[PDB]
Length: 161
Length: 49
Ligand SMILES: *[C@H](C)[C@H]1/C(=C/c2[nH]c(/C=C3N=C(/C=C4\NC(=O)C(CC)=C4C)C(C)=C\3CCC(=O)O)c(CCC(=O)O)c2C)NC(=O)[C@@H]1C
Image (cartoon, rainbow over all chains, first blue to last red; front, side):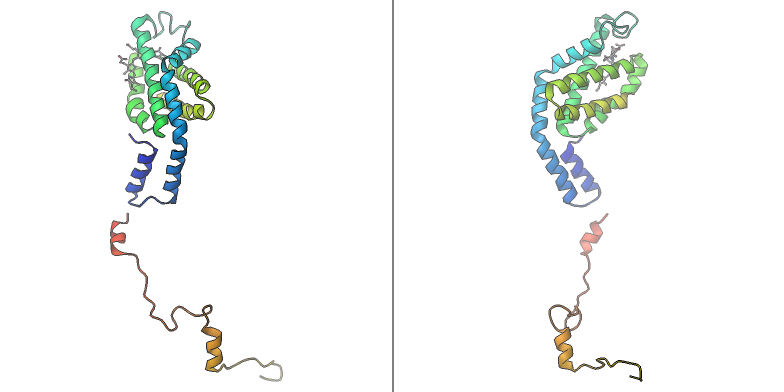
């Protein structure tokens, strides 16, 4: 796992070279985005449960998944799906705050598709739920922070697809 | 110069040549100076990837 600063540092180290102008510019860009990321993370922490609730309501209710036969049936499976969405939201917020997707790659994506295939859960339905979480988060946070969260959420969807 | 050549400056006195080619501009790096062949540091080369 690595934020933007650590990613730049590790890349420069692997080349065995100091922090040149490009690396300094990238670090300055991250520093400029830091306040935005902090405020967005605070807002999402404040409204984390509501975001998942609204996304599920507007994306994954009153359908076959909720109905018996769908993999969201029963309190157990519905809670598992809700916890999956909460995990997605929290880890996407982590990735947004760190300015890098390595945390998602090593803590989320690895084995996610394998477990989803093993348990037969709807990858398409999960993708749509992630979409709905994306719109809710964008609405709550704003435009630019919304896009920053959405890029990571779409990365999660692409990895899971 | 034959019957068809315009004359031209063929020789220069040393004083005139010095006036022309001894100013800060137009002075070669190697004329009256020890030119040390610049080379990257050996440790920099060793640590270079
Ligand atoms: C909800 C949007 C969709 C859905 C979800 C759902 N998932 C499971 C079970 C699992 N999901 C995971 C995935 C992860 N666990 C993690 O800790 C992380 C790391 C970031 C991920 C990605 C795992 C490991 C499981 C199995 C273990 C568990 O106890 O959850 C279920 C239940 C499956 C079952 O048989 O119990 C459900 C319902 N299902 C849908 O239909 C939605 C589209």
